[PDB]
């Protein structure tokens, strides 16, 4: 019995990629967001969209579109799962400087976390009685920033955590998935995750260990990464962790495909998606 379908998650990554790059303000972004909403609703979630016009670092006005999907919306004890769904507009880390003005698929950076969570949604919609409320949030406009400028990233999570869909929203725990699909990925303890949610990072990494995934979930320090979980911690006080492919042994910390033309379907590994999905589902089931 396989609780998390790696084949299905892989297909959700490919679906997103086949729309074209999900660049804020563009037609593939609108079409893919439409499909993400319809698909979450077909898996039994109550889905609402949170929209706003946000100013990006270069002055572009972006039509931000956060996607919020809920199971058992009346329950007071809730678990929060997160991923960003936009694609950075340019592969400005490509090894070929001529590519820094071009677009790329965002298969891992964007596709992988959404794909894993769509498959978890499919699983949740089949349960006959959830033991807690569950929210799945896909943040927009995470990846439109500038490297010297931390506030220029994670615009959708900053907006949502300051203006959530219920007043004073609380979840007991929050898990962010970012770049969880590439062959050879290494999930170390991200610093802010460990500093603010030691119990959660311990429970998740220990669950992965018990499932046989200690070759992916490494019990050692990783990077201090500003990501969508940090605004949630700071503004909502929810202990959140980030599961993210990162190692200080990597040239750019992130995997070698990050913000290059090689972040495309050929670097995606079903076994990495499975390790992450099976760990998350097991942890969720053991909370109830
Ligand atoms: Mg599986
Ligand atoms: Zn990125």
Image (cartoon, rainbow, N blue to C red):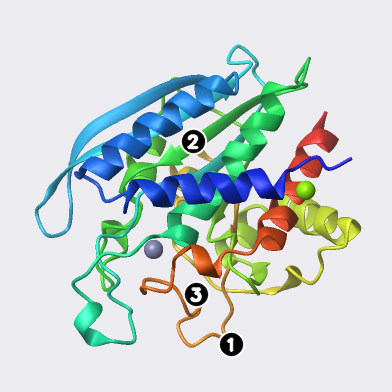
Residue that protrudes farthest toward the top in the picture: 74
Q: Nearer the viewer, residue 32 or 275?
A: 32
Instruction: Tell me if the residue at label 2 has its CB under 8 Å from ligand 2.
Output: no
Q: Secondary structure at mark 1?
A: loop
Can you tell which mark lies on residue 226? none
Instruction: Tell me if the residue at label 3 has its CB under 8 Å from ligand 2.
Output: yes
**Label 1: how many residues lie within 10 Å, few (<14), some (14-19) or many (20+)?**
few
Report the side of 63 relative to 175 (left or right): left
Res 194 quadrant in image: bottom right
The quarter of the rendered structure image containing the N terminus is: top right
**Label 2: how many residues lie within 10 Å, few (<14), some (14-19) or many (20+)?**
many
Relative to 117, say whether 246 is above or below.
below
Q: Residue at x 78, y 21 (%)?
A: 131
| Ligand 2 rendered quadrant | bottom left
Can you tell which mark lies on residue 137? 2
Can you tell which mark lies on residue 249? 1
Q: Position of residue 220 (x, y in %)?
A: 72, 75
Report the side of 99 relative to 258 (left or right): left
- Distance Cα–Cα, label 1 vs label 3: 9 Å
Q: Residue at x 64, y 64 (%)?
A: 269
**Label 3: how many residues lie within 10 Å, few (<14), some (14-19) or many (20+)?**
some
Report the residue marked by disc 3. 254
Q: Earlier in the sequence, mark 3 or mark 2?
A: 2
Residue 198 in view here? no
Res 35 quadrant in image: top left
Q: Residue at x 57, y 37 (%)?
A: 118
Q: How many marks?
A: 3
Residue 49 in view here? yes
Q: Earlier in the sequence, mark 1 or mark 3?
A: 1
Q: Position of residue 281 (x, y in %)?
A: 75, 41
Q: Residue at x 57, y 52 (%)?
A: 177
Q: Position of residue 125 (x, y in %)?
A: 67, 22
């Amino acid at each position: 019995a396989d609780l998390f379908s790696a084949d299905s998650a892989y297909t959700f990554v490919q679906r997103q990629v086949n729309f074209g790059p999900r660049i804020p303000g563009t037609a593939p972004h609108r079409a893919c967001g439409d499909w993400l909403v319809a698909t979450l609703r077909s898996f039994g979630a109550a889905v609402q969209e949170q929209t706003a016009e946000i100013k990006a670092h270069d002055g572009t006005m972006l039509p931000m579109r956060n996607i919020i999907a809920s199971y058992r919306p009346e329950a007071t004890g809730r678990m929060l799962l997160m991923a960003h769904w936009d694609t950075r507009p340019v592969c400005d880390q490509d090894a070929n400087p001529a590519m820094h003005t071009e677009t790329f698929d965002g298969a891992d950076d964007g596709g992988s976390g959404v794909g894993v969570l769509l498959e978890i949604a499919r699983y949740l919609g089949q349960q006959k009685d959830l033991g807690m409320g569950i929210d799945i949030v896909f943040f927009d406009t995470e990846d439109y920033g500038s490297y010297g400028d931390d506030e220029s990233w994670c615009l959708g999570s900053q907006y949502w955590s300051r203006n959530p869909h219920v007043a004073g929203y609380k979840a007991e725990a929050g898990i962010l998935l970012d770049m969880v699909g590439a062959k050879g990925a290494t999930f170390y303890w991200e610093y802010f995750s460990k500093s603010y949610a030691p119990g959660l990072i311990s429970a998740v990494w220990q669950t992965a260990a018990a499932l046989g995934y200690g070759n992916y979930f490494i019990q050692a320090d990783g990077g201090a990464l500003t990501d969508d979980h940090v605004p949630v911690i700071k503004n909502l006080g929810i202990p959140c962790i980030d599961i993210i492919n990162y190692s200080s042994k990597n040239e750019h910390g992130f995997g070698d495909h990050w913000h290059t033309q090689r972040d495309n379907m050929q670097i995606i590994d079903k076994n990495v998606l499975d390790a992450v999905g099976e760990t998350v589902i097991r942890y969720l089931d053991e909370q109830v």
